Image: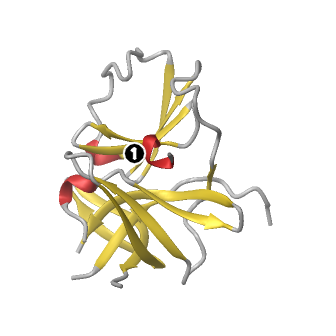
Amino acid sequence: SIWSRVVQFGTGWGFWVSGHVFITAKHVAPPKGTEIFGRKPGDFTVTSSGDFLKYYFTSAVRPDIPAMVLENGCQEGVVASVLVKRASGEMLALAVRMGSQAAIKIGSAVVHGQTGMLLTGGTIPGDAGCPYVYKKGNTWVVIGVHVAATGNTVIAATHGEPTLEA
């Protein structure tokens, strides 16, 4: 069901956080100016940080879904899931122990994101944009989008202002 929020997008995948909010890896997204989901620029606004790309649509695109919480990464040691879809429609929930912050070259330049360790009981380059999620008690929470793999290590791009200020 949460899997219906994961859809193909550009050269990778993206994730519906809510009916109005779509997130993806910037490096797989269609060019700025492209019509998406039958919507023209103007009907949506685009924000980016590093390899994190976020679309906000004025009118809901997926009215069938509730808003999920979007956090800026998670605590170290948290075991999250990478919701990997393949073009065949296959669904692979990859367990990942979230780690600390690293950088990596992605195309033109260097982005920064939260590393993670793929747990065995991996990813391929067309998996970029798939969501990292975890259950916080009763609530599913999205913490970022898949950017790249390494040798066991994955990187997630993150985004979001924490509710509480210092």
For this view, does 138 lie left or right of residue 89?
Answer: right
**Residue ID at (38%, 22%):** 37
List the residue tagged with mark 1: 24
Q: Is residue 151 above or below residue 165?
A: below
Q: Is residue 155 above or below residue 97?
A: above
**Residue ID at (50%, 70%):** 80
Q: Nearer the viewer, residue 19 or 10?
A: 19
Q: Nearer the viewer, residue 96 or 91?
A: 91
Q: Is residue 59 above or below residue 28?
A: above
Task: Choose top left, top right, bottom left or bottom right for residue 107.
Answer: bottom left
Measured from the top left, where is residue 129 in percent x and y? 35, 50
Q: Nearer the viewer, residue 91 or 160?
A: 91
Circle 1: residue type: Thr
Measured from the top left, where is residue 46 in percent x and y? 47, 32
**Residue ID at (58%, 25%):** 63
For label 1, the SS is: strand
Q: Residues within 10 Å of mark 1 (few under 14, many from 20)?
A: many
**Residue ID at (64%, 38%):** 66
